[PDB]
Length: 93
Length: 95
Image (cartoon, rainbow over the protein chains, first blue to last red):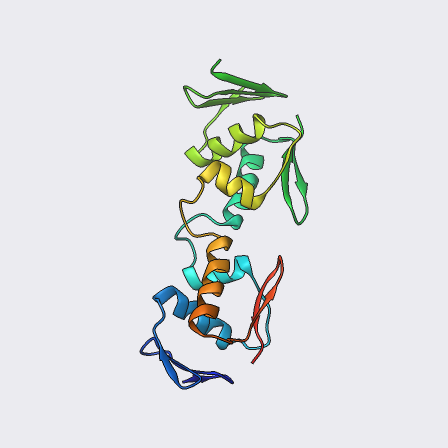
């Protein structure tokens, strides 16, 4: 079982006890709760939590945007898309 | 009317053809959609979240906003749950 101050979680059954009460969570709520509770004290980005809880490669993410920009660059050599590190992209001309 | 023209680049939105430096370029549908969007919005910076919505479609699939709302749902169902919101970054469970 996974234990925190307030939680007793059974990975096998989707069962959650919170401060003694049995709480009904959806499957995705459970996955998010278990992931955080299994990694106490650690900060996860919103992008990372989407990946870890909803899974990889089921739908487009911000990573997909980056990959598509790189593919455009390879197919159109010299394409004037500028990278703003930590933000996004701008086509110059 | 069908065309968007930028440096070295001709895009026809009706035939979905791209001519770059004199060569026809074979693109996937989403590569084309991204290129056409950027080429139609020269000089403008977009974040990755914005390009996701503008090019892949808004509210079509889970995003970081869905993460935010799920954290709120957990805090409602588990009153007092010790999830810390790191604004603009992510989340942490303290203990």
